[PDB]
Amino acid sequence: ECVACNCNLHARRCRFNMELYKLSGRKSGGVCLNCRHNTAGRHCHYCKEGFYRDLSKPISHRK
Amino acid sequence: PDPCYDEHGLPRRCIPDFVNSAFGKEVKVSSTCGKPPSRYCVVTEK
Image (cartoon, rainbow over all chains, first blue to last red; front, side, top):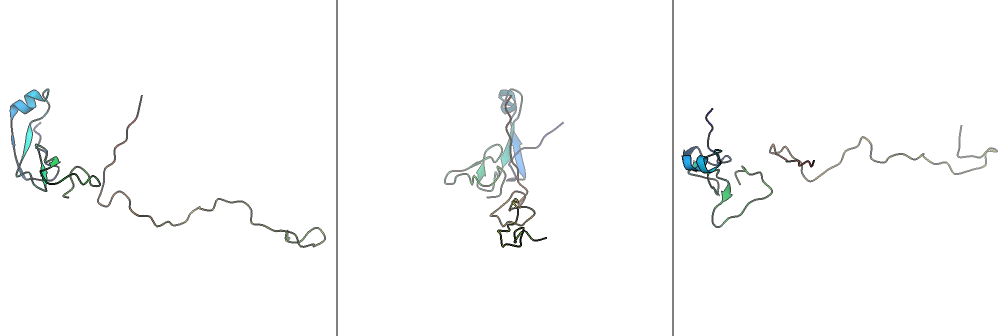
């Protein structure tokens, strides 16, 4: 099957690179587009420069 | 009849028996999972 990209509820568009999946030990290569909600990464999975992790909230919280 | 009075009705200590205090009652707390629906991870050793 196909599988969507992760932003942990932080984007509606994403892109892909094979080498990510290739070098992932054949596991994953999805990556956000407009990786929103003060998040960042291929999974919109970390707070960008200036911010930190609201540890109280889950990995996909809007804040 | 009445344990508050002795064999000859002499006034003696009558006491509620020993019971758990917290049984079937309400408690106000600070917070709880599920609002918003939340996750939680559990590790197990082997």
